[PDB]
Image (cartoon, coloured by chain):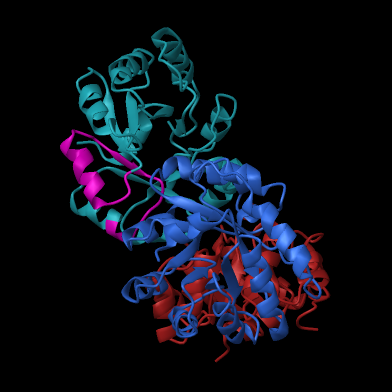
Chain colours: A cyan, B blue, C red
Amino acid sequence: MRDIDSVMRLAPVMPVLVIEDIADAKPIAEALVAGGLNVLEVTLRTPCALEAIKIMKEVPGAVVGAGTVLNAKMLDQAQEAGCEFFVSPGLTADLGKHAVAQKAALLPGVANAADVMLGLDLGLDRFKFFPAENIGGLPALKSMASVFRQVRFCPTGGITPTSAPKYLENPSILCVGGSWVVPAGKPDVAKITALAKEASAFKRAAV
Amino acid sequence: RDIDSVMRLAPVMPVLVIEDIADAKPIAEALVAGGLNVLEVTLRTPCALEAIKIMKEVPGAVVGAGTVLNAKMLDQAQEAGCEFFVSPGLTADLGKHAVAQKAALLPGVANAADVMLGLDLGLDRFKFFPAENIGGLPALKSMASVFRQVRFCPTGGITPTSAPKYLENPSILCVGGSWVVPAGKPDVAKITALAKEASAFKRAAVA
Amino acid sequence: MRDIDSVMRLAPVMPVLVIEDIADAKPIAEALVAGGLNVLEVTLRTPCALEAIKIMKEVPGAVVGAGTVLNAKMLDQAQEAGCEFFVSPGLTADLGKHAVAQKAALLPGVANAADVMLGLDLGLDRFKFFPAENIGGLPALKSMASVFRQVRFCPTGGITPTSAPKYLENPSILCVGGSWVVPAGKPDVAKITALAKEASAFKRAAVA
């Protein structure tokens, strides 16, 4: 299936989903897909997360992945649930070696040059710049992209509707991760779809 | 004792710098009398190993070593009787040595790759260090939101008025602090008064 | 011959060179040496970078190194090109292990305590603080230098002519990395030599 570069190009914004109630999963996936945000990152931060992946996987148009993958075992459990891609807050050689060996579409987080160097040693060149606003923001990413010209990025962490277009004007950025499209209360599918359509319209220099 | 239990004993772990060996016993006595029985003695001073042996004989003191940079320093602190060990950062070498030695290590972390390295080694308790140069409480709040099973001790720039704000987060078990021992000759009544105030800090993690 | 500590002490500023045209390599190296900045870091960020290193090495007095070295094979390629030192944005165990094996004067980037501890475990004690203005600046470097008292640093990343003396007042700092002496665009050899002479006169608490 798709490699992580192809996943990143599909939509300007990758929603970062924290499912506290399993009944929220289907309405959230349907509303995001209705708004054109087809790429869904379900963080493995809650007990029902893997079940939420199995529910969202059956929504037509949804490209479901697992976030907060911390090790090869969690990548395996998420892949067995049907995840098409995997995101991690940071990178280890054991996690990256396992993803390459399994041909899993992994998007590891990086915060500094040594993280990126470990990723390049493993054959990876696509990373989440995370957590963006705690590690110097767009100016820090602009410098890191200047050092690693063959790498492309997905900043995540404190991104907003106001700052997302600024990141997306950089050619080295393919998309951003975002939490604002689904507010942490009970889902409102109309509001979620309207935020998704608004984010769907964001300009991308790289696409 | 394991590091999670050590962190839960008191809201503040004093970070002690003993330059005058004569100060060690009165300081540890005053801190214990004030309810701060967990003592981190930095190894940087020449008399630090001798100070650890004196503090270990104070009843109720739980004495550990700070600024542990490598396996050799850990072995020296363990030979001196330290019950726990604190490092500014984490290496695979120091971590595998602490696990093999059954040493209660509390390694510093600054980013997700540091945490994931520790989790791969079996560690899940970390010092968030240097806290005020890596984004403070807002950055720690995000990191704790990602690593739901990890618990932290922020250290580096913590003050008596900022410490309660960190302690409102249940992922924070305690803070490290330098203010409980004022510079100059020890005033045992003043140290015990500051210690009693710190021992009364409320924390969401421990009733 | 030279270890990385001796390279850092040669001049207050190590220019961070990005060569977009091979024809500019010789004039830039000659202009820098004429201004007294003999230590030249050619970043491996453009395809012609290794070719530019071979050209600059022929300028008398030039001490040529490679920057943005990402792995052990890249260090070997830069060494075969004639580099006398090597700079890396970060540190991996594989890169540091190969550098110590080959006695290569490596200056690896650090941003946090785990980076420094990995370098110390390899026997390294000289690091660039990079990228300085995105990882907390001088206040962050001050705290890190007070943790690792035996380590000495080269801050790089957003250093300016105004801020370089501020960093160079700290005795834990041996030099700074800078881009302002040879910025982007076609070289101005008169401007480069003049900026190199001003950088050469920067006071240093550590070196004198």
Residue appearing at x 31%, y 75% in the figure:
B100
Instruction: In the displayed orientation, state which residue is furthest to the left.
Output: A80
Q: Which residues are magenta?
A: A69-94
x then y, percent, for residue A71: 28, 51
Q: Quadrant of the N terminus of chain B?
A: bottom left
| Camera-side residue of B72 and B17 | B17
Q: Position of residue C117 (x, y in %)?
A: 50, 73
Residue C2 coordinates in the image, percent (x, y): 58, 89
Looking at the picture, how far across and down is residue B22, in whole percent? 72, 84
- The residue at 19%/45% (across/down) is A76
Number of numbered tags placed on the structure image: 0
Instruction: Determine whether C181 is above or below C72 in the image.
Output: above
Q: Nearer the viewer, residue C58 or C172?
A: C172
Residue C190 appears in view: no
Depth check: give the residue in front, C147 or A192.
C147
Q: Is residue A99 shown in magenta?
A: no
Q: In this rendering, would A94 be left or right of A90?
A: left
Q: Tell whether position A85 is magenta.
A: yes
Give the residue at x 34% y 32%.
A41
Compared to B38, does A30 lie above or below? above
Residue sitting nearer the eye, B59 or A179: B59
Residue C151: name its quadrant: bottom right
* Residue found farthest to the bottom: C1
Q: Quadrant of residue A106?
A: top left
Asked if residue A183 can be seen in this view, the reply is yes
Image side of residue A165 versus residue B179, left or right: left
